[PDB]
Image: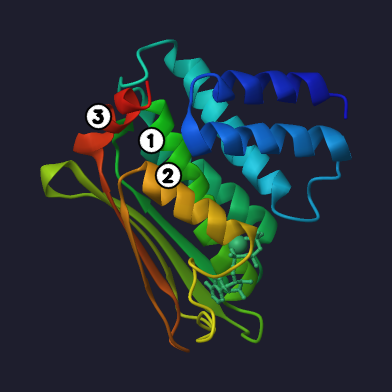
Amino acid sequence: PDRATELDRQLAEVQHRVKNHLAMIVSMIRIQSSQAGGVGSQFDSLSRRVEALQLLYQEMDIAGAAKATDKIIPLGAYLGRIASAINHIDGRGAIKVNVQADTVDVPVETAGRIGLLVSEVLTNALQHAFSDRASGVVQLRSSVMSGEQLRVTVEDDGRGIPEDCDWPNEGNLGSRIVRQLVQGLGAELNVTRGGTGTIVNIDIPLSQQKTLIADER
Ligand SMILES: Nc1ncnc2c1ncn2[C@@H]1O[C@H](COP(=O)(O)OP(=O)(O)NP(=O)(O)O)[C@@H](O)[C@H]1O
Ligand SMILES: [Mg+2]
């Protein structure tokens, strides 16, 4: 409310370095922020999505300018700060959140897509997986494998995604975000259900990111 124009300036700087669905997504977030004008943003996932984009802006600011295809964003650092914010706000006693992120530099567009992705899925774990549970575990992993394949995992031991619900093909706004960003990353998403929990795995080709980013231009 005192940072409205500054927040908007940051989200615009992000917006003007990205494209396609991602750029659109940032555009929406910018508008919705101003409408509430604060705060205004905390009662739903808006605050969370703003924070993912601000944390990304901070990484860009530190990294300086470079070609859209240049690997300049430290993903592990960025995902760690997303995860920390989420467990701090949306966490709860008796719920353990482990975080294991590899050191890897990626392009801005790649980071933004993955960051929002992790925000969506991880929030989902803490918000939904433990409704009726007294204790739980969430694990976030980000592992570089062979052939520049990055695997991002979010694991619950909680309640499980309802069977009728075929997330992320079905769901609320979060599910639509996830499907778009996965597509923009050239990635593959998979989900595993049950009362033993929800396991989400996104396989991302970091080798193909340069190609994706330049095709958008
Ligand atoms: N880890 C999980 N464990 C249990 N249920 C889940 C989990 N993730 C998602 N769900 C369920 O799937 C639904 C769809 O989630 P989603 O598409 O992200 O929308 P949402 O989280 O409800 N609202 P939004 O803030 O926009 O994401 C949720 O409402 C939950 O009922
Ligand atoms: Mg959600």
Residue type at mark 3?
Thr
- The residues tagged by marks 2 and 1 sit, at their Cα atoms, a distance apart of 6 Å
Choose the circle earlier in sequence order: 1 or 3: 1
Residue type at mark 2?
Ile
Kindly identify the residue that appears in the image at 31 percent across and 30 percent down: 105
Kindly identify the residue that appears in the image at 55 percent across and 61 percent down: 175
Location of residue 203 with respect to 107 vertically, above or below: below
- The residues tagged by marks 1 and 3 sit, at their Cα atoms, a distance apart of 11 Å
Contact (Cβ within 8 Å) of mark 3 with mark 2: no
Kindly identify the residue that appears in the image at 47 percent across and 89 percent down: 195
Location of residue 110 with respect to 194 vertically, above or below: above
Which residue is the extreme one toward the top?
Answer: 65
90 on left or right of 209: right
Residue corresponding to mark 3? 211
Contact (Cβ within 8 Å) of mark 1 with mark 3: no
Which residue is the extreme one toward the left?
Answer: 146
Identify the disc placed on residue 114. Answer: 2
Identify the disc placed on residue 110. Answer: 1
Choose the circle earlier in sequence order: 3 or 2: 2
SS label for mark 3: helix
Q: Quadrant of ligand 1?
A: bottom right
177 on left or right of 203: right
Residue type at mark 1?
Thr
Q: Cβ of disc 1 within 8 Å of ligand 2?
A: no
Tell me residue 168's x, y (percent): 49, 66
- The residues tagged by marks 3 and 2 sit, at their Cα atoms, a distance apart of 17 Å
Viewer-proximal residue among 31 and 111: 31
Dividing the picture into quadrants, the one containing residue 154 is: bottom left
Quarter of the image with the N terminus is top right
